Amino acid sequence: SGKMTGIVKWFNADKGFGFITPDDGSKDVFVHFSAIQNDGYKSLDEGQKVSFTIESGAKGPAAGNVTSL
């Protein structure tokens, strides 16, 4: 299980970026709407439980299979 569960706090669709809050990862990582898991109609809730895999593209953390629980 190379995956980690967490919850998204904030996320902007106007710019194309957001910030998630992983349980084990008390820290905060950024996410994008270019690797989500919600069919289509890009849309997410504030303070929702979602999983990921901390993907890399810029620095270190960055979305990574963002799916809603």
Image (spheres, grey):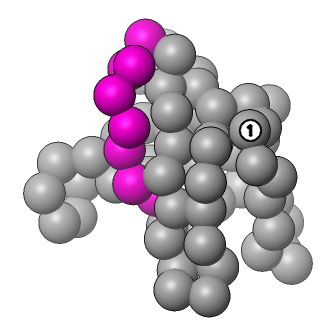
- Residue under the point 48% across and 52% down: 19
Q: Amino acid at mark 1?
A: Gly
Q: Is residue 20 left or right of residue 25?
A: right
Q: Is residue 47 above or below residue 42?
A: above
The stretch of residues the image draws in magenta is: 24-31
Point out the residue furthest to the bottom here. 14
Q: Main secondary structure of the magenta part?
A: loop
Q: Nearer the viewer, residue 38 or 18?
A: 18
Residue occupying image coordinates x 27% and y 46%: 61
Give the percent coordinates (x, y) of residue 6.
58, 26
> In what element is the residue under mark 1?
loop
Q: Is residue 52 above or below residue 23?
A: below
**Can you tell which quarter of the image residue 57 is in?**
bottom left
Q: Is residue 58 visible?
A: yes
Q: Which residue is painted at 72% across and 55% down in the image?
A: 37
In this rendering, position of residue 51 left or right of residue 56: right
Image coords of residue 38 (percent x, y): 81, 59
Where, quadrant-wise, is the C terminus in this rendering? top right
Identify the residue shown where x is 82% and y is 52%: 45
Residue 16 point in image, percent of width and height = 52, 80
| Residue marked by disc 1 | 47
Residue 30 within the magenta-colored segment of the rendering: yes
List x then y, in percent, for residue 65.
54, 48
